[PDB]
Length: 336
Ligand SMILES: Cc1cc2nc3c(=O)[nH]c(=O)nc-3n(C[C@H](O)[C@H](O)[C@H](O)COP(=O)(O)O)c2cc1C
Ligand SMILES: O=C(O)c1cc(=O)[nH]c(=O)[nH]1
Ligand SMILES: O=C(O)c1cc(=O)[nH]c(=O)[nH]1
Image 1 (cartoon, rainbow, N blue to C red):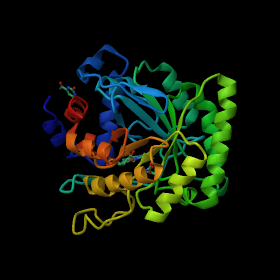
Image 2: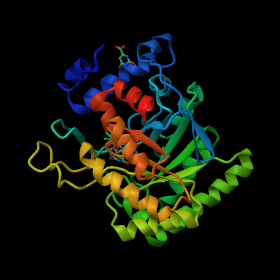
Image 3: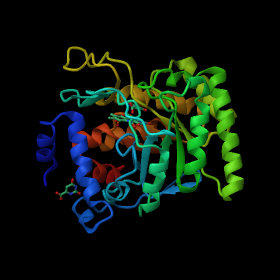
Image 4: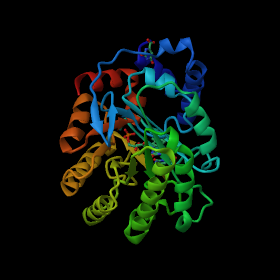
């Protein structure tokens, strides 16, 4: 049916209850013939990035399908790639509810989920049963109780288990909803993490006889100097790619709006400009040494093209998918 009516109905429910209802129906049809109800034709626009071939530049950002339960249904919708997760070594409930809020007038969202997921072992089993033909990205992170200074082991543990089933691996060290998680992107802490990750990738390549690229997901709340250091570190350690950007703690564009003071990360339209400008500065520093996957407030063909012009090789969407639904996918892929 007409998505606006779909949205109209969904927006009457609590934000998370709306997501749970939606995924309840998707899981109900994913991998079955019902899948035709959400499927849509999309032209192919192949892009080579990180040694991989993406059928099209548009991907589903991480956070929607955290446990990889609806890979096939979502894929049928047209996405060139799908990023599942964030997943942690052990299952965890996440923060207390409510943890998700809508800013309808700003076409944005604020969340403090806290990595609510069923664990990496469960996710691996879901992936084994999926038939998706696009690129599958697996996004991983640290369990809440794991001391952030020993967080590196949680990443390595997940890497060992998903290596054989991932198109690329996404390292999440930018979530604002896990205490201390963002500290991992600064100084020696970042260098030590990247050193371990690249070494683990090296061992896994010898074990599985194949190279699985790794991309690091950074926050949008980094200063010019910090952004330069991160970019340089990524280059020195030969990281395969960088995903910019995650949600922001900034609230300067949503003052005076309902839920504007809720704690958490802000996404959607209010993140669009900040995100694009970070991509541009990032791209300037990287100087083509490694690709950028741009994400943040993309809600139209032009917004996507702006990210590409700023320097991104690929783009992902989340919030915009919730406000504009399936039609957005078709629009971007068709005209990007
Ligand atoms: C409800 C929700 C859950 C998310 N969970 C994650 C997650 O688990 N892992 C991750 O890397 N990013 C997560 N994000 C961030 C998105 O993947 C994306 O980086 C950010 O929302 C910017 O894109 P958007 O403006 O198009 O939503 C989440 C965002 C939202 C709104
Ligand atoms: O009702 C439809 O046709 C429909 C709904 C939806 O969410 N996606 C799609 O491609 N079609
Ligand atoms: O699950 C979460 O709380 C979460 C993770 C992340 O990386 N970004 C975000 O906005 N929320």
